[PDB]
Image 1 (cartoon, protein in one colour):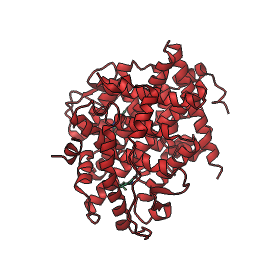
Image 2 (tube, each protein chain N blue to C red):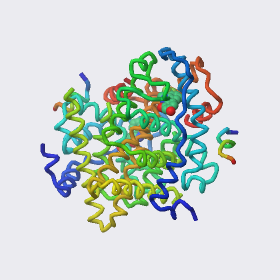
Image 3 (spheres, each protein chain N blue to C red):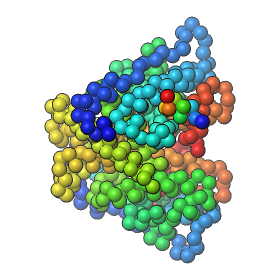
Image 4 (cartoon, rainbow over the protein chains, first blue to last red):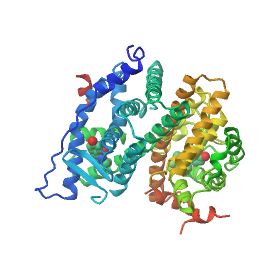
Length: 236
Length: 234
Length: 10
Length: 10
Ligand SMILES: Cn1nc(-c2ccc(O)cc2O)c2cccc(C(F)(F)F)c21
Ligand SMILES: Cn1nc(-c2ccc(O)cc2O)c2cccc(C(F)(F)F)c21
């Protein structure tokens, strides 16, 4: 393969290069909105963000080496997680605010689902206090992609490959922290701190996926065909 | 301020090992549970009696007692199913393809598909157990991971907890270094172990959804404690 | 209130 | 069959 032969700095350069763009929402301050319309803003934004995430996933080292069936599965499991960590990353420099899009800033008081917002706000607040680096962010985001659905025959050969690639990203994270002058103790701690966030991001995803289900059944918030197929695989 | 920080790594290990809750038994009924009423009745009953021990265990976790009562309640409400599950997959390690809920209650996936939704929860629990067995997970590592879950899972919803979490991280690294692992093997294994916690969270949320559905269907009665744990979730 | 409030007390 | 499948296959 090629993912295993990459150096830590090559790994970082590859991930930074593959970074998806920041899209705008359809939000209009002169247009009235409703609980359902504001929800439509998020789902619509997420829908065309998925098309960029797919091309982003292809450029993640080791991902394209996997079978098309496994690639589909990994994205069906982590797409909301990846979206959320992307949200809290760009929401860091906005205390008490969530930056869904450059033209869409929402705080806790616009809780159309306060609980999910507060969790996202807390996660973003955690990143701000840790002074999360962009290099660390793209590592964490790629970890989520490869890890979120790795636990669902010669298929085991692929599982070990993901484990191998995951170990590479671990060394890459440690490489960054060592480069940042952190002591060996601080490197272990920061690594642990960063990965414990992923447990919470997974939690926020599961909570969000349940709300996404209710929006489908209530049939008032527009859900694209792709989002429906994403949700359907999660409720399989 | 908190005693947990003055603890050495070996003292931290000894504290967690000594605070370990017992392995409880299910009813000595030799009947193989296939009905959803019979199986889930045994799981909820087992969870009920285990929750009392978990509470007692939680108190003896360094740093947990230093928190306010409300914070202690919150952490247990968030992580109790995670803690039960990581305990399940731990003692199920030596029984591949099987889940050791109790020494007299082993469940395979063939029993799980006699209950709608459970067979995927079982498969996820089986995969976690096999993953633990392949990493050669040690008991000293297990008690650290379980305490991490207790302290981490509810953190957001405060510097002290983060400091204790760092101590456990130092404790985990300490154990691996005692086992002769190189520095690279130390941060790789640490990363691997902590990535399992995301899946444990996933299984817990899925398990909480099934628990809620049982309360709605009303056929398996739930104890007041399990109901209050479930309400806290939703 | 909660049973957890009581069981955590001793 | 899936949209995600078609887009990954591109
Ligand atoms: C809570 N949440 N957050 C998003 C979202 C959209 C775009 C983005 O870049 C990040 C996000 O978290 C999102 C998209 C679709 C549905 C939901 C919800 F269902 F609420 F969980 C969502
Ligand atoms: C899925 N699951 N698993 C358990 C359980 C009970 C005891 C234990 O030691 C470990 C467990 O995972 C359990 C207890 C109560 C309810 C559920 C279920 F609802 F299925 F999620 C449970």
